[PDB]
Amino acid sequence: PIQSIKVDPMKSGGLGVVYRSPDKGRVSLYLYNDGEDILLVVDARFDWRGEQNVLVLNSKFAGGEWGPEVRPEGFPFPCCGYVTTITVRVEIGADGFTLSANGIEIVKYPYRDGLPPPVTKFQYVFQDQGASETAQLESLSAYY
Amino acid sequence: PIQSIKVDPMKSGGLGVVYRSPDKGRVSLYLYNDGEDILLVVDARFDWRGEQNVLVLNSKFAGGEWGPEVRPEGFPFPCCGYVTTITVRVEIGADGFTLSANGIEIVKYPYRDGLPPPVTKFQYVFQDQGASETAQLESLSAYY
Amino acid sequence: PIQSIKVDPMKSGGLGVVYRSPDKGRVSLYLYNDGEDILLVVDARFDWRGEQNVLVLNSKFAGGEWGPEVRPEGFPFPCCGYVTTITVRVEIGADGFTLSANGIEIVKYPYRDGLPPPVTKFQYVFQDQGASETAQLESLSAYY
Amino acid sequence: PIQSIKVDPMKSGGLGVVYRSPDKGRVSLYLYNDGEDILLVVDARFDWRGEQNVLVLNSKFWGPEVRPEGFPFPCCGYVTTITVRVEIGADGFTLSANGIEIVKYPYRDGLPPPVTKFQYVFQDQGASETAQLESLSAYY
Ligand SMILES: [Cl-]
Image 1 (cartoon, rainbow over the protein chains, first blue to last red):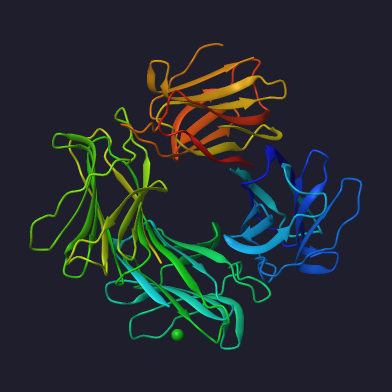
Image 2 (cartoon, rainbow over the protein chains, first blue to last red; image 1 turned 180 degrees about the vertical axis):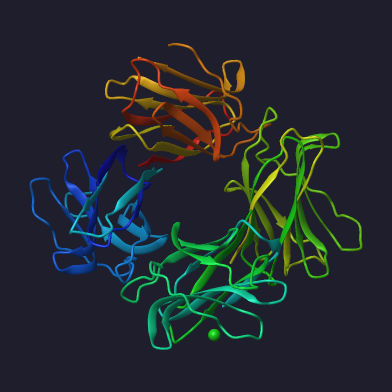
């Protein structure tokens, strides 16, 4: 349900994850620096606090408050309560993060004030909301 | 919008397709014998004849009539009018075909009476129903 | 040891193979048009009629003689009589083929005059020469 | 040419690497615990001090060295993409390359999982084509 890989400080390249989606709950991906600031959360809400199939991007300092949510369209939430295998990729660009899902680009996310790279940790968190089918993590990768 | 591969008669291995889903229309995959009978259609209805996110599998002889529809759950249609990359595979087993999408097994389908392998041809067909994102075929594969 | 796909007339995309290499003998990939001209042969000689670890490309008319033979470097022939899986890809570009193996571009190859695409058939052929490990075909693909 | 991923300690699953090979030098893959013990190194010697195209496995805190056949060192001057996978099984590591099993390596006393670190290290020895790391993976 929770796994991380820590990388040698990363200012370019990509982080990827493959997982089987849950019918309920949320899958969260956290990109941290050593300060443990959240440079980016990619928070895919399957069914979460009354929201269905909602993707949320945000950042924040370690003991800190969420910035504004961004909510892109195009994340491959399966219909009808189904589940599937999802591959997600975060490019660490000069500009900001680039998020792709199944090789399709979802959103460009410019780096937030005082939170640019290097990334040093990439974390998967599945949180349940009484799902019939819970998320299964298959892999975590760093792309150089 | 229509593309096929022709193979030496296959009685095992697999046929795969990758494509970018459409927001409307249907993507059907046809597996034929040398007689041009349809041993199997894998009919992914994204938005077709007032149906939405429906998978239909059936068989019929060349000029004949469709037999009994099977409508399995789990095919990973995207929510919300979104598109994604879908990988589908059909194994040709001893007793039936095994259909999988994104590496997850969808259903097993016993060969219909007098419609057994060998498969000799595997064809992708997308038919529009005024989609704003039309299907894009990426590849067709034969597995030994 | 011989397998082929016939595709619809292809002026675009690519064609792929995946196989487990032989410790001797040759593996040839032929690209035909409808007339059965050889628009390209990618002939990988592991141990063949005097030669070891040599790559040969040519084209010929169905009738006629060969052309000037090109022998690129870079083809991943394994050392020491080992075998491995080889992935090979032939892009059908505007001006010639591009050959790659395991994702590394091996050579570009301008179309011989009188022998441009459409390509209508991609064929794999293994010919033994007393291998302790013969080749095994894993897949053939058309990319659009 | 040195990279690592540190993972929450793993007693099952797998570690993968993809890189483009060098024509000289060695690329070495290390599996470490918390104390930097070498639970296993997979040392692909393309051209390394007299040895050519040799695979070497071992562990340390040296000890007996295994030398499996079948690792896909390319012939001639050549380089390619290589995909190596190491499974953390119950009996030991299982190592494969380009989808093919190369050998099984029982854990050695004092050196069991969990694995906390997987590290790639290319050391050059005059290569005209240097190694290029492409990705490092953990499988769960
Ligand atoms: Cl119909």
